[PDB]
Image (cartoon, rainbow, N blue to C red):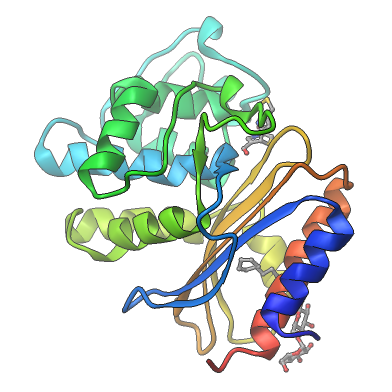
Length: 265
Ligand SMILES: OC[C@H]1O[C@H](O[C@H]2[C@H](O)[C@@H](O)[C@H](OCCCCCCC3CCCCC3)O[C@@H]2CO)[C@H](O)[C@@H](O)[C@@H]1O
Ligand SMILES: *C(=O)C1=CNC(C(=O)O)=CS[C@H]1c1cc2n(n1)CSC2
């Protein structure tokens, strides 16, 4: 397998699209590998981790409770939304909504949560407050996935997303319990978690949130490490590629393989 940077370059050339990547030490924040780390990519569903960071902050401040039941209507369902659709009659707790948003990529759940944090503008304000002056959410579901070429709306950079995730998980911005909850939601991802585990060698920790969008947009924000420990934050985004979903997944996996085989740094 090529060196990580060489594999990232190869992936970009094969996808005929832009790849953005950062590998960051979780404990120290040190950048280990970076490719287009300051370039903008659509967040897609990956924004939902930051969203639930804002939710947990409100819980910590006493302005929210994970137990609080939110009741909604059929008109609030924006697409598929399998969990939200199932609990239409009885509602869902704020905690449940975050679980659905993060572990099952439920889009209606994300909108309901956005309505508790002051919408996209409220979430962007939260980001500015924690020192992220780059990441921005502008739209609700489902429009935030549009991924128009050169459109800055609903984008982050690999560097900013990695830094923000580290802040939310480790910095004491959130309480101990809230930090633990956000991590557990990522550990519990049902969309990609199990699949990734099925192809990871024994001993490799994974927690993640993935995203998909228009024009080949694809993304993953993850914690990864040997000896069953979350050693590193890895963020990979793809954009403006005509490639199949299958190849896009294969290329991201290929970058992961390169990281595993060249782990010591
Ligand atoms: O010497 C290291 C390892 O080399 C191989 O492991 C392979 C594995 O068989 C393959 O399935 C995977 O594909 C990579 C799949 C990664 C899954 C996605 C990872 C995500 C996580 C972080 C964000 C982006 C990538 O590569 C590794 C390394 O070559 C051997 O199979 C294994 O016995 C050995 O311990
Ligand atoms: C997040 O990246 C996404 C959320 N979930 C789903 C789904 O529940 O069907 C599919 S992948 C992706 C996404 C892309 C688009 N939407 N959701 C709604 S419109 C385009």
